Image (cartoon, rainbow, N blue to C red; front, side, top):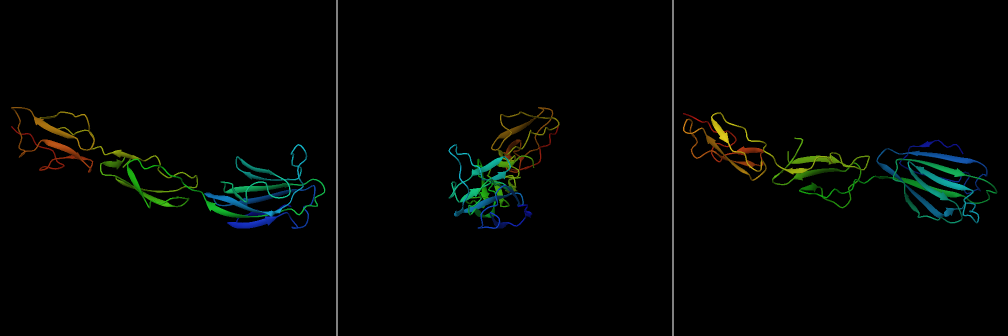
Length: 246
């Protein structure tokens, strides 16, 4: 046969000279190369499938098989199609091999391929919501995941954006929603902060001073809490820390 490479997103091809009998004792090599992220879905009219059948052993002599990376689709032989009309290779690249033997004198085969975007499946939202929230996400689709109230994205915020990739995996799957961490309390000169059980959201700490050498200058300050800002804050002083004075 010796066909050229097939770049086009959609196409079709048959048992050469089709529907003349397939020339015995020859090998047919056909190369489809899509662009990565696009599986080759193959459609074959069973009435467009005629091949010299297998023996008692079920061993297919005349053979048409498909090479999809580690996946092998076949081995196919006979009159009338054995598998389904629709085949998902789950591959961007595909090779069609047709092996001929003796008394070709069978109509042959004819098929079409259409490329289909490889889906990036669902990661169950632990504490988050994806937008847009739909039923099936595929290649190139873009999503904004937004962390809830009390949760933040580690390696930074509360919102991030990810595509579905050519590998069928979401970009930045690594990033997840932890409860927000204001960190360890910063310490004040002439003052002691008594560390708590949680540096997380909702937690409360209170500063104290070296008594009776240094004192408040607060106005009711001292007590701080971890807010969604990722910072300990006071209702009066806010993000800033007390000053201890003689």
